[PDB]
Image 1: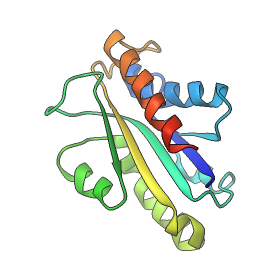
Image 2: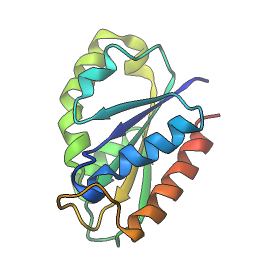
Image 3: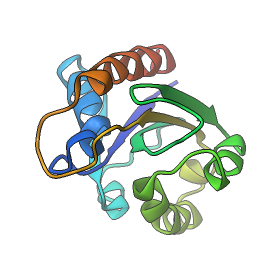
Length: 148
């Protein structure tokens, strides 16, 4: 089992960089992390047949409070993103991810996991809010479990 972590988000929009910060922590810990940001086609050059993909992103929700973390996998991800969860970022990646899957059967069949970190302040700035720092920590914990 080889796991690839995809970190999504925009670091210049405060909590919208939560995914990237979690990714950087995982990268420092030795994990295979691709910083996608807002461009899924970065994956074309990076993917190496990994059987599990763990996507980490900043999200907006109203059922949940800031700093909260969600974790979905498989078909469940797309059912959730319909109503409950909002990540502009993964949404911006879906079409490109679909194309890359059409071009690589390993990617198409890979196990997909989504970790969403509920943002509080998605305004201009490079620092995370205190509530989302806590969220980054738990997102990192979930991802380490998925990456055995």
